[PDB]
Amino acid sequence: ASMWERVKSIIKSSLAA
Amino acid sequence: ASMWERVKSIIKSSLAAAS
Amino acid sequence: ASMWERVKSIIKSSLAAA
Amino acid sequence: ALTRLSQPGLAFLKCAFAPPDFNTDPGKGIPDRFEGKVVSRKDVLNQSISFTAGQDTFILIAPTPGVAYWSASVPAGTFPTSATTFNPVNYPGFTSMFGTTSTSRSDQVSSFRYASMNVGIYPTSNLMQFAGSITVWKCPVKLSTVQFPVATDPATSSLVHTLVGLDGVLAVGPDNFSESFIKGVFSQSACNEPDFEFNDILEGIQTLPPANVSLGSTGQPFTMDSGAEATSGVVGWGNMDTIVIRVSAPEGAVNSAILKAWSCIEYRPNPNAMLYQFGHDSPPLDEVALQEYRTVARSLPVAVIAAQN
Amino acid sequence: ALTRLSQPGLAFLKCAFAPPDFNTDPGKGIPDRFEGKVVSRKDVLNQSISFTAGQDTFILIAPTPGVAYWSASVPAGTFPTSATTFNPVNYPGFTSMFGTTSTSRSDQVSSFRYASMNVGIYPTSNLMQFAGSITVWKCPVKLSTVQFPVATDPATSSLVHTLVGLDGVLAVGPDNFSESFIKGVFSQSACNEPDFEFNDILEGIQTLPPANVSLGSTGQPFTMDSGAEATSGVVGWGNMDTIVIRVSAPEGAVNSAILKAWSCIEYRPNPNAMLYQFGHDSPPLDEVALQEYRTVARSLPVAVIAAQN
Amino acid sequence: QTAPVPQQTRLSQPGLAFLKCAFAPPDFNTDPGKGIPDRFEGKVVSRKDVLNQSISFTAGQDTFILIAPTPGVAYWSASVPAGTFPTSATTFNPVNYPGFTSMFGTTSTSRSDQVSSFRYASMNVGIYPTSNLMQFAGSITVWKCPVKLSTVQFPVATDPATSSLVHTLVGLDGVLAVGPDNFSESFIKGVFSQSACNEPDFEFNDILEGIQTLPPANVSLGSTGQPFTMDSGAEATSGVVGWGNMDTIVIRVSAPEGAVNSAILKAWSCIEYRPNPNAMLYQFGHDSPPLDEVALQEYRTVARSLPVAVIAAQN
RNA sequence: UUCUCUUUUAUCUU
Ligand SMILES: [Ca+2]
Ligand SMILES: [Ca+2]
Ligand SMILES: [Ca+2]
Ligand SMILES: [Ca+2]
Ligand SMILES: [Cl-]
């Protein structure tokens, strides 16, 4: 339940395609 | 020469000209 | 001393960090 | 080759240069850095027009939202004078977006940015009656301001909107397309900026120069009158050059045609607008499309005939 | 990945999306083309606040420098009306930045540009007192102008600042966050432009509509009042969408909470200012960071529960 | 027991030219510049403005010169007692670049007759001392100011009561003190300095009509906030046609008592304008050069690398 | 967060 981590996720999710 | 065809020519001629 | 050479030195000094 | 463009990036380019070649929805947005919620407006006008003989009719397509073009006729062989006033014709549903009062333009949307701006003229007259020519060039018209003092009590300084570069309409630009009327014409305008900046919606503008302002206090060469605030008006000015068209109808010439207008615009919708319901994130960056756009534009002619379109 | 980003680029993305999560302001500038002299300032406001029962309190977070937010309360179940006026709540040291007179705003700095603009609400009420809801949406409010004639002697045409797209505050847009008050909330805003351009500091603005102007002639739905020029004022309008928040308090409910607001702003320091000695160069361009920003931004939800920020 | 709420490489020709016009124009036999290798590639006209001014400085005076992004005007000058800075009592008068009128008419409402908008590519300036070594005395000090052209909103008690809005310059207060980031050195050693785009990109600014003075006519300097005044003079000889996105260079020449400070001042400016089809300039038009990423970043990097200014022996 | 399946639009290519 963190904020920074939801940002670090949308960054490594779009950098995978 | 339609407008879309005059356009697709300049683009593909630009993609191949830059190569 | 020149000014164009001061710029050519900065262009090659940063284009060197690759 | 054209597979290096994102879906929207291609869509974008079609609305930009050839929207008559497609049935509908030519664009889904601008594949630039911006990806906030916007609305893709495909403005299209179909206006049947008859040109008065002996008159050199002048038409502007320039980036006033909702209003396709502005026209006015002047004695053959002459240009607009201080005595000339241009009157807007609007894309279907102007009021349905900008209200009916000069202070309710920002009700539906708050800002915008044009992507495309095309126009075509198709001759409808016969080959025995027609005569004349269609000349075309584009002017770098921007919307600025004029500062001058007024002797009121107390004495004060005013400041109002003034159009710079209108002076380019009083003469046929060196870079231009000119050909027989019957051959019609097609031409489009592009962003006159290194990028797609957003412009705000403008409230209260119905005439330029404004009401209570003397022309050429402005240093504008002629006047712009949108008319009744309840029918038309000036809601903004996009970063697009304006297309100038001169159709010179000689004496006894029967020149008529059908005019079409295209305009892809991204508006920023207000949540209180029903219009908002059709919002979608602007297309993400498509560096290729943005580079092609620039190249293609610089490549194309001022204009071309009807059939070539 | 996280390694392609330069220090400034990573830091930038942090001050922009998750500031509470740090013991210190990561922000060190905007990784864009511009590398001139600037001054990074992270404005943080902390404020114990208690809401009026039987009254819906509206809060705007909007890109006005020095001022955290603007509030106003209205009757429960209603929205702002022409009779409503929002009042500012400054960030610490407003005066030390923009003086105490409406004409000494640009004394320290000349222009600016926002990087981030966050906000959070942390309920402090016990489970036997809290009641109500928290609704949140964002409006594309831009600062434009309105032109209208005035019957003075001689007659003249005025022109003043107007807030466009303000009307969006009178309806909760389909895209929104809405949850029980007790669950609090967190939301951030981002650049509503394809690039980070600088905006000039505005002199003399204390009210909108300004003095001697009727709300009717501006189109704005309600009024903005910063109060005594000696304590607050409007120093400029950034390129960030405005965060709207409706907090509904039932009759007889005790809604207490803490309110926090972040703002990473980059200003152009004046050589004379005592600020200058703190400036540095804007961070160099970071393609990756600028792309992550756009993507992350459009990907994140309107707002989230106060529990996670 | 509370139910959740359901939510729903190398540089190009024009690119290298751009870097030369931008940082070193005295070092070339010709205007290297050919346009801005930025995204934009529309119709433009490249103009290389150059002014050569022979000048003597009032002794016991601190003469202040300003290289500002004002098309057609090289710089603005005014002198105050040595040891002091401009006051409300000061007014700067511009020195026009060659052919100001041939470009912007002779009416305060004729500025946009030739061109509609513009954007500065570079703005350089140099001072050369013609004074004999013994006679001269003093110093030259330079710093740059982020002067932007804004607006001011104030009410006016007329009948009926109204609210005014006029142009006002913000960032001028920075001239009333020597910026920490500065170049200071003996007058005789001369100086050379240049400015750069204070924006992440080269957007076009419009041409402004009717501006002759700032504060404008009928406006008290107290209303604007500006620290001093700007007077362009007769609308038929000069004026303010626009304000580019370039930081403004400030130069303070300190001439002590009995000091003979003579020199030459050159002003280099290359600007890209949008020509009006009707104008006689249109015939020299060419399209902005295509984007050149290399140049657009070398520019940014070089700019931040170069010192505030250097002595004239190294221009 | 994971694949199949039909979807069902939508362009690009002959
Ligand atoms: Ca004019
Ligand atoms: Ca309104
Ligand atoms: Ca821009
Ligand atoms: Ca001041
Ligand atoms: Cl507190």
Image (spheres, coloured by chain):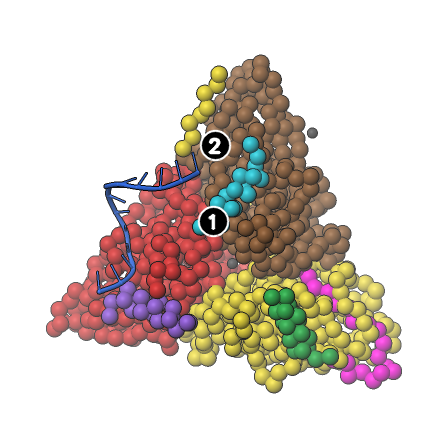
Chain colours: A cyan, B purple, C green, D red, E brown, F yellow, G blue
Residue E48 in view here: yes
Position of residue E293 measured from the top left corner of the image (x, y, whole percent): 53, 48
Expressed as whole percent of the image width and height from the top left, the position of residue F289 reads 48, 72
Tell me which residue sits at (31%, 66%) in the image. B8
Q: Which mark is residue E177?
A: 2
State the residue in front, D223 or D14. D14
Q: Is residue D69 left or right of residue F177?
A: left
The answer to if F98 sits in the magenta stretch is no
Q: Residue placed at 41% from the left, 43% from the top? A: D269
Name the secondary structure under disc 1: loop
| Number of other residues with Cα within 10 Å of mark 1, as a class: few under 14, some 14 to 19, many 20 or more | few
Q: Is residue E7 left or right of residue E150?
A: right
Kindly indicate the quadrant of the structure image that contains residue D137: bottom left
Look at the image and say whether residue F143 sits in the magenta stretch. Answer: yes
* Callout 1: chain: A
Query: Label 2 amino acid?
Result: Phe
Judge left or right: residue F172 versus residue F253: left
Mark sitting on residue D264: none
Task: Give the magenta-colored segment's residue range.
Answer: F128-148
Mark 2–mark 1 Cα distance, whole angstroms, equals 29 Å
Nearer the observer, disc 2 or disc 1? Answer: 1
Asked whether D64 or F7 is in front, the reply is F7
Q: Is residue F212 above or below residue F261?
A: above
Residue picked out by circle 1: A16
Q: Does residue F96 show up?
A: no
**Disc 2 element:** strand
| Left or right side of E48 for E145 | left
**Dot 2 falls on which chain?**
E
Q: Residue at x 50, y 43 (%)?
A: A10
Q: Position of residue D160 (x, y in %)?
A: 50, 56
